[PDB]
Image (tube, rainbow over all chains, first blue to last red; front, side, top):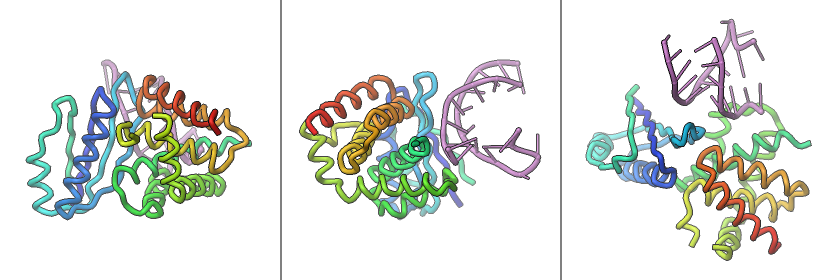
Length: 79
Length: 132
RNA sequence: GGCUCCUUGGCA
RNA sequence: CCUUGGCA
């Protein structure tokens, strides 16, 4: 089972700092990551995509706990 | 002459960017990006590979150079790795088409960040090359 | 031409 | 249907 996450923000440095934290949290809990892939800036909006290809129960817990800046909006899909 | 290099620079930036964010083996990360982009052309693959292998081998001196025209961890992820790619190609590969790399590198930054980031990178990358 | 590929947004 | 890009 995998997870796909897309992050968006109107501040690109804040965005990439958010992606880094997620990656660290995921790896800290025994998870495995693919990406991230940066998408083209569109209408002043920066976005990134990240795949979680391996995860533990601890990984899900931590992702639920994490409080991202409100400016960073998250979209999560299991598959 | 030498249009395949534009896509190769995009490939290489993507790798350095995710190397910076993940801190895993560059070789394996390069393989990920190649697969994701579905790169088939031989010269596109090989120039991208050379770009990354160069940036990685000389990472310490590259960073030291950049820091002389600024600490490097203050920069954003897009800005810092674009600068790394640029210094790699212009100086450690001694590009004979420096005008092209400036254009391509700055476009990369504009594409994944914004105009401001693009101008900061262009201005820093210029001071660097000027010194060279 | 991508009916034998992905990606972004707008509309609808 | 139009559009940002990748593959190029």
